[PDB]
Amino acid sequence: SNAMAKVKIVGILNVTPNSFHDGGRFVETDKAVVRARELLSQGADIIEIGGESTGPGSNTITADEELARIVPVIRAIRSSLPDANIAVDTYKAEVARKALELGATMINDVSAGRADPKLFGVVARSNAQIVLMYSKDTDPHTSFDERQYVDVVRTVYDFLAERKKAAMSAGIPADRIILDTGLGHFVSSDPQYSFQLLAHLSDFQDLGCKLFLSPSRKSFLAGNELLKTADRLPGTIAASAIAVLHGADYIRTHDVLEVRRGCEIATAINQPPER
Amino acid sequence: NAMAKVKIVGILNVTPGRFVETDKAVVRARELLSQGADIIEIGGESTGPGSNTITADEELARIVPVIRAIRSSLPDANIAVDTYKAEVARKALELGATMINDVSAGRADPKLFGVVARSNAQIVLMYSKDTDPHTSFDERQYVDVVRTVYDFLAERKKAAMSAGIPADRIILDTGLGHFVSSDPQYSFQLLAHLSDFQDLGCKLFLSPSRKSFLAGNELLKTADRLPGTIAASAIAVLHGADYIRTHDVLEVRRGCEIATAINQPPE
Ligand SMILES: [Cl-]
Ligand SMILES: [K+]
Image 1 (cartoon, each protein chain N blue to C red):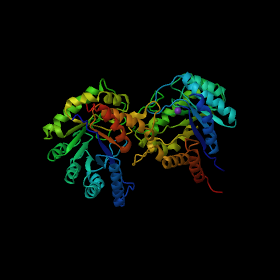
Image 2 (cartoon, chains in turn blue, orange; image 1 turned 120 degrees about the vertical axis):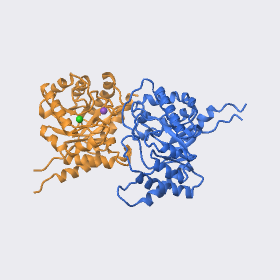
Image 3 (cartoon, rainbow over the protein chains, first blue to last red; image 1 turned 180 degrees about the horizontal axis):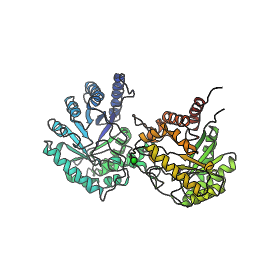
Image 4 (tube, each protein chain N blue to C red; image 1 turned 45 degrees about the horizontal axis):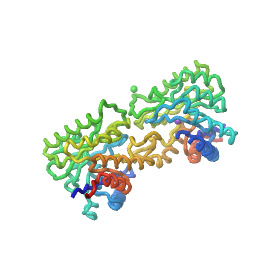
């Protein structure tokens, strides 16, 4: 029949220790597992585990520290929740390699394969999907910068087409390549460009890949009131629903319950009558 | 011998119909005073990242009814106005404000210094990395942020005095957060070396006030920045701050009292 599939909701699971010094890792691992269960309980389809933040102001960490953070978490989830689908947010080949050996089935590379020349190969030799994100910066840690564009849609489309080609040349087929236009500071600290990408998201379907976006209480949702993170849930729901309406196949979020429910409405609007 | 406590400046933002704002504004003003604020700083125009310009008429429409309401209901309240517009400062001073905080340090409106010169009010000159009063998201780097900010404040104090404002009515703010840089390290460096600014001979005013430079390694959002704000505000006082601007009057006043006590020499 003509049934439109629901969007896949990607729950964000960031593993960041509280204590700066050594010790207290079992406690942090246990906390991450509890959060993973809650994400699944709220209806997340994929749990995206990351040990290194890449938003503005974020610190770079070594592959060893990154693995020390996520490995115990991945192992605990795969062991107790084997039904759960795990994605790993990393730009390092060594980290991706280990994550894939442990059962992760998706790698989300904020640098679209530019940070580590070996990452595409690692993904190619697995059956994992790769999410290629557009970023205005070469460095995987994005900057606060009010970048301007003549036409952001063209710039991002051209970048994603080139990264898709590069991934395919490295051995990853098109059916395992997912594209993310980026939103917020990854695109620009000037919010207009994020809204323009959302308006024209359907144009990206021509690249022949599933689409992944993360409005997720980002900067661009501040609006006229200059709303801070705590007040951006309605805007996050609206932007995520509109993204689904315009073609998003995956929505990444910290607010699984609410964003899943808002996106269900977008899917229902896109659902043609059963006749 | 007894060192005076810092003056706490309570933030009262009047940024959104119109009339539904004033009784609520008076209620908040009363609460700021109840918590121990010495000055109520009314601001009708946001100047943080992503903000846009509002007209002088719109700014006046926002703040004037609030100033009038506070003067009437809370006559003992000292009022400051956060504005870069001469026309707005002029009206605020006529109505009783005794302090004008200019995020542009007199650069945005060539007539603002003259307006303040022709009053008995104090002016707060803040350092901003941008010429436009609405600050940008920009990870501005510096070879020596303390030297850059010090020289900027010196030049601005000189301009204020040239316009007719005496040194005893000039207050300096190094800026913190995005005004200095979207890279947090520079805000911490200014707090470390705040005592160096005492050489300019003016009282010092700072506003850590839950700014994003306080996010730290955990990338803490606003709701979780109170401990950092308390620590930063207390260290600012320890290092020479005469005024601390905040939304959290009670807690910041109490934390700052500890810094004052640490600065109190023995008997
Ligand atoms: Cl420099
Ligand atoms: K303001």
